[PDB]
Amino acid sequence: XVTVDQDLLDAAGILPFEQVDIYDITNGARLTTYALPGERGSGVIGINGAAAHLVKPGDLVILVAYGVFDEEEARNLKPTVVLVDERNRILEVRKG
Amino acid sequence: XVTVDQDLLDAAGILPFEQVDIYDITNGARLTTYALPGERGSGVIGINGAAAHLVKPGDLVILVAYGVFDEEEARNLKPTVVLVDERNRILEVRKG
Amino acid sequence: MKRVMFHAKIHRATVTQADLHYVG
Amino acid sequence: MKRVMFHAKIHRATVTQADLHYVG
């Protein structure tokens, strides 16, 4: 895979090549793939590969990244949530 | 995602934001998401996001958390199981 | 080797609400 | 024990394109 505007990756704190899950709000699909850096500022969210069977252009989705934490760090984690508009421009970022 | 009465999270030993799987007893769906702390004592089990396509209000479910253990710890693990009523109030907690 | 183990669960809970278009 | 936690997400993004036969 999924090409993502790198601006979004930066805001999310998701690295290129990191595994991500895609949960489709439009149709309910759920899958696992990875992120690829996309043109900055383009707002690109491109589904490459087999995933195209499940996630279509125009779909609303949620891209989630999970990490492996130690107990202490887990308890102090404040996840990052990036909210975007219909063009995938950042509206707000929440933490925790 | 899944909002869970924090009382339940505490009893389970599941942390806010921890990844959890949801296995639907009512319809057989199986998915991965994460926990969000819900109002204590409300007995809330709320399905947010794409998951709503698969898990509906009224469904009976199982929320499972998996961890990564060292050999020694794995062999001495006594998992926590929280049993609840129809309102998600705790009936009993088992370990091991 | 590290093992992936089941460590906790809430068994037979009832879903009380759903919000497909939740924002958060 | 190590825990698997949600650490980040892009919420309610819109898919802009698709390429089933992408090469890369």
Image: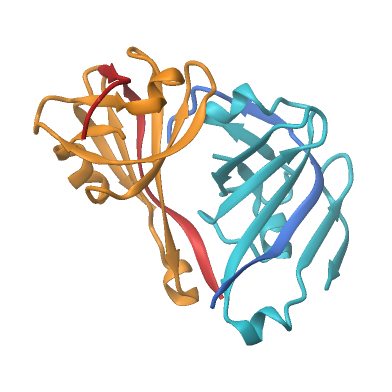
Chain colours: A orange, B cyan, C blue, D red
Q: Quadrant of the C terminus of chain B?
A: bottom right
Nearest to the observer: residue C5 or residue A43: C5
For the question of whether residue B39 can be seen, the reply is: no
Nearest to the observer: residue D17 or residue B17: D17
Task: Answer with the quarter of the image where residue A2 lies.
Answer: top left
For the question of whether residue D7 can be seen, the reply is: yes
Residue C8 locus on image (x, y percent): 71, 62
Asked if B78 appears above or below B46 in the picture, the reply is below
Give the residue drawn at x 88%, y 39%. B86
Nearest to the observer: residue C10 or residue A21: A21
In the rendered image, the residue lying farthest to the left is: A40
B47 to the left or right of A91: right
Give the residue drawn at x 24%, y 51%. A15
Give the residue drawn at x 73%, y 50%. B41
In the rendered image, the residue lying farthest to the bottom is: B72
Give the residue drawn at x 61%, y 25%. B52
In the rendered image, the residue lying farthest to the top is: A58
Asked if C12 appears above or below B19 in the picture, the reply is above
Residue B79 locus on image (x, y percent): 76, 69
Residue B64 locus on image (x, y percent): 69, 53
Residue D21 locus on image (x, y percent): 29, 21
Task: Answer with the quarter of the image where residue B25 lies.
Answer: top right
Task: Answer with the quarter of the image where residue B31 lies.
Answer: top right
Q: Quadrant of the N terminus of chain B?
A: top right
Marks counted in the figure total 0
B75 to the left or right of A10: right
